[PDB]
Length: 274
Length: 10
Length: 100
Image (cartoon, rainbow over all chains, first blue to last red; front, side, top):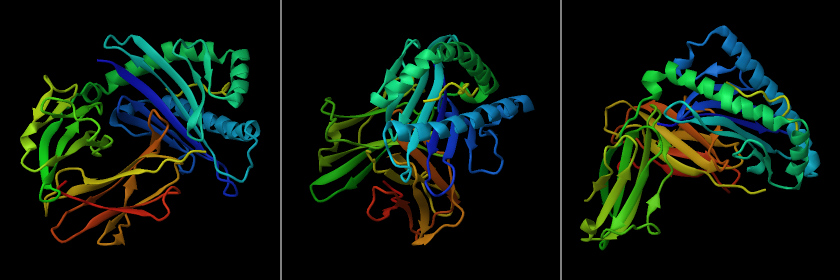
């Protein structure tokens, strides 16, 4: 199926506590493979997946330089942002960045991303056509004009459709026996009386990969959306993921409710009934 | 491969 | 600014059964800002050796973090996750419910 490479970086200013903290991580699909941390001693891009170890010293040299360079420019961008928003240098602020590309089954390019967020909200982003920018506000528009003048978009576009998809293609091959993997969820149901006339039905999905999944409750064959509780998908820590959906039901009416599970690793969607 | 971020000046 | 409260889940990697080795997880997501403290507690006391993942975020820009430690569940031992964040007037302590 399709695949993605993504880089996430977070810069956090610490007034009266030294330089801003910079943390970058790299993902192929739902598997992390590298990290960088400006507060760590190594001061290098570190491997966080087995299949990336097989990269030579050059790779680690190049990647380390790029991510270190980026930390310094986002460091400065935090300064520049204070100016644009007329904010004091006594407060702490955040600069987030996502970058990456998507490829189909045939390894062909599908989509590219280059996005920034200041204090948790959109700042500037490269549109889907990778030709123009989306400025979120008055401040980001200043940057947008700069990036237009400096032709940043054409540079990033080429990199996304080229270097990125080529890098993604290589990573997949190297992480073949691990990234082409598709683990179906093990499902089960729990049941607990909330009181003398009500019980909780909780639908479980465990040990699946990738993380993408859909858990749905129906009552008498009809989606029971509003009344449901649905937790965020969570990492088990072993490379697989977990999730559950719960409904509060009248005691003795358990059989009316059905849980429906959709996942890439499943031949057909599952149905669970207590 | 980490992007080239030189021109990402705000 | 706009702040977002962490969503806290405490759980074992595998379905817990006494005597059998396992991993204790506390997963905090959907929060902002990113600076946050997360500790695992065994019968009220802070576990000293707890590891965590590298800071990362979702599509909506909200951060997520996994804290974990190896442990062997017993009938008597109680566990909880203490999350300290600016959106919380006092640290949120969520108990581990092994059979939910």
